[PDB]
Image: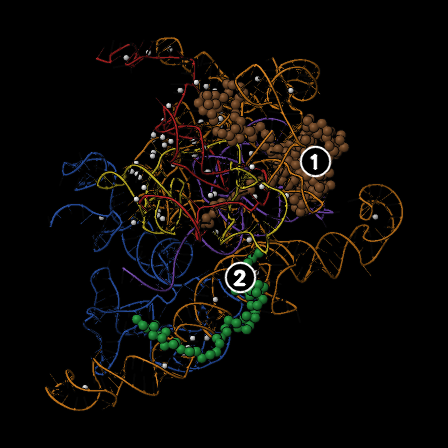
Chain colours: A brown, B green, C blue, D purple, E yellow, F red, G orange
Amino acid sequence: GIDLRWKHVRSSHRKAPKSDNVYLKLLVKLYRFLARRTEAPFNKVVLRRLFMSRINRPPVSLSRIARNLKNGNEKKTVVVVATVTDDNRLLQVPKMEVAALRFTAKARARIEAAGGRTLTLDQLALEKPTGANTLLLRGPKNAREAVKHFGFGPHKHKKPYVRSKGRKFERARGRRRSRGFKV
Amino acid sequence: VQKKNPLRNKQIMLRLNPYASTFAKEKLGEVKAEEGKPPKVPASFKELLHEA
RNA sequence: GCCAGAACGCGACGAUACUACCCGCACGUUGUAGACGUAUAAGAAUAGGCUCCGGCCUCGUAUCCUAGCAGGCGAUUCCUCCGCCGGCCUCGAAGUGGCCGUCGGUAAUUCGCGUAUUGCAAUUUAGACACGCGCGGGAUCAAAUCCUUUGCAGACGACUUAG
RNA sequence: GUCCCACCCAUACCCCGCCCUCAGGGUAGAAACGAUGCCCUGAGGAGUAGGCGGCCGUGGAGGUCAGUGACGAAGCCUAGG
RNA sequence: UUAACUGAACGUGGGCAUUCGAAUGUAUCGACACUAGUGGGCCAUUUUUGGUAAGCAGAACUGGCGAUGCGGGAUGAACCG
RNA sequence: AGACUAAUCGAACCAUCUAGUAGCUGGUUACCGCCGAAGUUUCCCUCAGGAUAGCAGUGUCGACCUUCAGUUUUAUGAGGU
RNA sequence: AGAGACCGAUAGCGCACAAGUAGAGUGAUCGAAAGAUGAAAAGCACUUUGAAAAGAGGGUUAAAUAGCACGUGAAAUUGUUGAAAGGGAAGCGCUUGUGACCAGACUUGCGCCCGGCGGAUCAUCCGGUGUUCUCACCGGUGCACUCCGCCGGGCUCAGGCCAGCAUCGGUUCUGGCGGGGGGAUAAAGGCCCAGGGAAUGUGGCUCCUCCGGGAGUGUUAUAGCCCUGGGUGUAAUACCCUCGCCGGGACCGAGGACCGCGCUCUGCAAGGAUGCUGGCGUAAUGGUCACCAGCGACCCGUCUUGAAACACGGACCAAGGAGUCAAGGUUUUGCGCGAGUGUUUGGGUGUAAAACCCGCACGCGUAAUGAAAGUGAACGUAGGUGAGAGCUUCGGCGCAUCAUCGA
Ligand SMILES: [K+]
Ligand SMILES: [K+]
Ligand SMILES: [K+]
Ligand SMILES: [K+]
Ligand SMILES: [K+]
Ligand SMILES: [K+]
Ligand SMILES: [K+]
Ligand SMILES: [K+]
Ligand SMILES: [K+]
Ligand SMILES: [K+]
Ligand SMILES: [K+]
Ligand SMILES: [K+]
Ligand SMILES: [K+]
Ligand SMILES: [K+]
Ligand SMILES: [K+]
Ligand SMILES: [K+]
Ligand SMILES: [K+]
Ligand SMILES: [K+]
Ligand SMILES: [K+]
Ligand SMILES: [K+]
Ligand SMILES: [K+]
Ligand SMILES: [K+]
Ligand SMILES: [K+]
Ligand SMILES: [K+]
Ligand SMILES: [K+]
Ligand SMILES: [K+]
Ligand SMILES: [K+]
Ligand SMILES: [Mg+2]
Ligand SMILES: [Mg+2]
Ligand SMILES: [Mg+2]
Ligand SMILES: [Mg+2]
Ligand SMILES: [Mg+2]
Ligand SMILES: [Mg+2]
Ligand SMILES: [Mg+2]
Ligand SMILES: [Mg+2]
Ligand SMILES: [Mg+2]
Ligand SMILES: [Mg+2]
Ligand SMILES: [Mg+2]
Ligand SMILES: [Mg+2]
Ligand SMILES: [Mg+2]
Ligand SMILES: [Mg+2]
Ligand SMILES: [Mg+2]
Ligand SMILES: [Mg+2]
Ligand SMILES: [Mg+2]
Ligand SMILES: [Mg+2]
Ligand SMILES: [Mg+2]
Ligand SMILES: [Mg+2]
Ligand SMILES: [Mg+2]
Ligand SMILES: [Mg+2]
Ligand SMILES: [Mg+2]
Ligand SMILES: [Mg+2]
Ligand SMILES: [Mg+2]
Ligand SMILES: [Mg+2]
Ligand SMILES: [Mg+2]
Ligand SMILES: [Mg+2]
Ligand SMILES: [Mg+2]
Ligand SMILES: [Mg+2]
Ligand SMILES: [Mg+2]
Ligand SMILES: [Mg+2]
Ligand SMILES: [Mg+2]
Ligand SMILES: [Mg+2]
Ligand SMILES: [Mg+2]
Ligand SMILES: [Mg+2]
Ligand SMILES: [Mg+2]
Ligand SMILES: [Mg+2]
Ligand SMILES: [Mg+2]
Ligand SMILES: [Mg+2]
Ligand SMILES: [Mg+2]
Ligand SMILES: [Mg+2]
Ligand SMILES: [Mg+2]
Ligand SMILES: [Mg+2]
């Protein structure tokens, strides 16, 4: 006997994509080579985010990009391993260059109409094989309707599972002091 | 590919400790004590020993 | 004393056809809880014994036998040791030993010829009992069951009887 | 009752081989690779109720082997591989 | 708040490894999501309640059997290894 | 006599509602690999049953965060066996 | 009337057949089993045995191993033949033995030299055509020391099964020998020097017995013993610790060009076994089965704290036999589009239940909060502080997310 608390412990993180996209497999082969033959920490981060599922790759809009193009980042290259969407609230688009996994049709048209350019993640590896003069951006992970229901309980202020909204749907006993108690 | 044991294989011992050959050649494990006529127990160490 | 009698315990006796039996020879188509010098007889005491009558005993750490082509062929030499037969005695706990005779073999001494080639190891195929087969000689000419019958017996078999 | 030597054997301990599981590395100016492959290194392996992974079989459907077959398809028997 | 810029909380600027201020390990850090089975237990050293007592009935800390083979106790769920 | 009403009577026989309901007994079909329990808390016309917390598996994500610990040491509190 | 990713005779309707039939009940009502010779009956003429049913011959057929008890013809259970075991169950696990039966492997291969035989045309150059643009193919030349094939002879190397010896590597068991250190620098002890004692009193002296002896007396004499110092002496030996050197056995050989650390450095025992030799080339090694032998081995499924249980189900075999489908929720994986998204209620069209095309409404989402009348999201570069991957002109900028103060 050896008296060990743990044995045959498996890793907690993904080691390959779960998708079967043929072109995503070509992209993964490229960045496996780059991460092994370069010392840049940038390349290792991009490889890991290519394994992730869609709820771990939330979208990023043009407004969120414009917020981070201030205070001396006007001429860096924006890198987003996700979809880039359009924002109707933003009326004037600044000029920029962005490398993204994919663009929506209107997002791509507004970037180029302001004098910018759009790249693919394989075009980025050819121009910046070490990730120099770049900024990495992520979208909001918790801005999902399902996360509002997590951890429901007393004195937690979370969202309940109900079939409708109105006065007759879970508002009487346990929600106000005029009927028993409150939460 | 195969661990070999010094204290049985002399070539391995010389690889790890180049002073081994000198130690054996000069017989450093058989050094004699310094000369000198020794005194005797001072006649009261012996009295206490058999005291009771 | 009295009842049963091991259905895988034993003894004595009678008659034994069928080569079933006996003797001799030669083979293996064979089996064996396991040959390889398968060598050794006093009785008794243990705080006492043995003896050749001189002595001797912790001790079988003994005694016998033991050489030669897996053991040849001759000589020199010796009168020892071994075996198959035959004749007399002897042996009863589950039957054994001794004496004598003919015949065959035989380094206690010393030699002459032969050994190879199984190739640098491979069980040293070797003993003793059983059994089978084939010859050549001797000896021998028997019973049991069914069946019929009895009632000293009996569910049926079996049993006591007669033909 | 107390003390002292030598010896016997567990799936336990030590060394070696092989299987699997987990972990960590190498491999493109490609004389290059079932890159889902190959090469190097270390540790681990008991299990009911229960959870997950990978694989083997059966009846039908699309595609493909320009597949087998009356010179013998399918089925059945076989101390033969 | 105090008679009172006197205090109370939160700070700018500056100084201090010439040593970030016991030992050992790190053979397994943090946070989240979804769900299975279970909800009759029993045994033992020490401590303990009722009972004359019980292979009786009831508790505390820890270790076991249940869910588990192997070497010992001839046998022997729980004892020794 | 709760007796008899076609071997049927303390409420006949036949078809349908009907696959009537069961906190209760019985069964529930190939292989290998890795991890691995509970009989305890609170509430219930609750005591052979449920919900709820714990114990277990699987999927991940954040950094590979000087990060932790069924342990010792040093200083300093509480307790009525 | 047309069809199907439906079932294939214990299935599919109760019924693929003279099936709502045969049969049961007074009656209302209940209600089965049962498909397949061969292409064609060519469905066995004649002889013989038997009372007959039938048998034996002889015919038909591609086949009677298809004869109306009819395609194929499994298991439970039974007969004959063959092999084997058995002293109050049998069956099973590990490991030898005997008997029977059996799959592989091996039979040669490449190379060099010598001779014979046959055929070409080997190298080079000229013309044409391809192609990876320098590499090839076809036609012509070549014409015996070149090229190709066969046969004969010799030589090296590699090759199948089981074993023996020598030199090494890894692990381990077990004998023997040479040194060093320590303690009261072992303690004792032998020999020598000086002092002091006694008795289980040596020799002498006395008494008792001659009957072997005994009893007194006293300090080394004709034996000896015990204490205390000193010398040889740093004596020896035991015990504990430690540095090396020689023998004897057992099990194992993973890896496959070189590369490294080293040494006793023409080389080697240094990042894992080679060299030499014999027998046999097949049932010899090896495998399957049956049986005897040594050791081991309680009947499965299930409920249970506890099952081999005097706890329940199970005589045997074949075929059937149990977490499914729909609507509505939820979390997680893959995919399309993305502030939007969803053609298919319907219309157009068609090679016609397919595939293709169209867009008015509508659903979910884009805004909340109150019982309701109602009202309705920027002081600031969409705020300040502490952490924070990544980038950086090295001054800093700071995603996601967490804690905190505000709007
Ligand atoms: K009220
Ligand atoms: K001779
Ligand atoms: K299938
Ligand atoms: K003030
Ligand atoms: K639960
Ligand atoms: K529960
Ligand atoms: K109970
Ligand atoms: K009890
Ligand atoms: K036991
Ligand atoms: K009736
Ligand atoms: K109940
Ligand atoms: K007290
Ligand atoms: K039927
Ligand atoms: K009738
Ligand atoms: K035919
Ligand atoms: K015929
Ligand atoms: K047939
Ligand atoms: K040794
Ligand atoms: K000494
Ligand atoms: K002395
Ligand atoms: K005297
Ligand atoms: K290895
Ligand atoms: K049961
Ligand atoms: K039973
Ligand atoms: K989904
Ligand atoms: K809409
Ligand atoms: K940073
Ligand atoms: Mg282990
Ligand atoms: Mg008898
Ligand atoms: Mg396991
Ligand atoms: Mg089907
Ligand atoms: Mg066939
Ligand atoms: Mg069979
Ligand atoms: Mg229960
Ligand atoms: Mg109790
Ligand atoms: Mg009880
Ligand atoms: Mg249980
Ligand atoms: Mg246990
Ligand atoms: Mg045991
Ligand atoms: Mg006992
Ligand atoms: Mg009646
Ligand atoms: Mg049902
Ligand atoms: Mg019912
Ligand atoms: Mg485990
Ligand atoms: Mg109630
Ligand atoms: Mg029950
Ligand atoms: Mg972090
Ligand atoms: Mg980590
Ligand atoms: Mg108290
Ligand atoms: Mg139809
Ligand atoms: Mg039928
Ligand atoms: Mg039917
Ligand atoms: Mg039929
Ligand atoms: Mg006939
Ligand atoms: Mg046929
Ligand atoms: Mg029949
Ligand atoms: Mg038939
Ligand atoms: Mg049969
Ligand atoms: Mg048997
Ligand atoms: Mg030519
Ligand atoms: Mg060795
Ligand atoms: Mg001395
Ligand atoms: Mg000395
Ligand atoms: Mg090898
Ligand atoms: Mg040979
Ligand atoms: Mg054999
Ligand atoms: Mg047994
Ligand atoms: Mg019992
Ligand atoms: Mg029951
Ligand atoms: Mg029964
Ligand atoms: Mg069927």
Residue at 73%, 29% in the rendered image: A92
Q: Amino acid at mark 1?
A: Leu
Answer whether labels 2 and 1 touch (C-beta < 8 Å).
no
Tell me the element at label 1. Answer: loop
Q: Are the residues under marks 2 and 1 on the same chain?
A: no
Residue G316 vertical placement versus C120 (above, below): above
User: Would you name the residue on which mark 1 appears?
Assistant: A69
The subunit letter for the residue under badge 2 reads: B
Along the line of sight, the residue nearer the viewer: G345 or G310: G345
Whether residue A148 is visible here, answered yes or no, is yes
Query: Residue G250's spot in the image, x, y percent?
Result: 47, 60
Residue at 56%, 64% in the rendered image: B13
Query: Residue D31's spot in the image, x, y percent?
Result: 71, 48
Along the line of sight, the residue nearer the viewer: G360 or G41: G360
Label annotation for residue B5:
2
Residue at 53%, 21% in the rendered image: A163
On the rendered structure, is A169 left or right of C91? right
Query: Residue G216's spot in the image, x, y percent?
Result: 15, 84
Q: Amino acid at mark 2?
A: Asn
Q: Where ligand 41 lies, by quadrant?
A: top left
Q: Residues within 10 Å of mark 2 (few under 14, many from 20)?
A: few
Residue F28 vertical placement versus A35 (above, below): above
Along the line of sight, the residue nearer the viewer: C42 or G347: G347
Label annotation for residue A15:
none
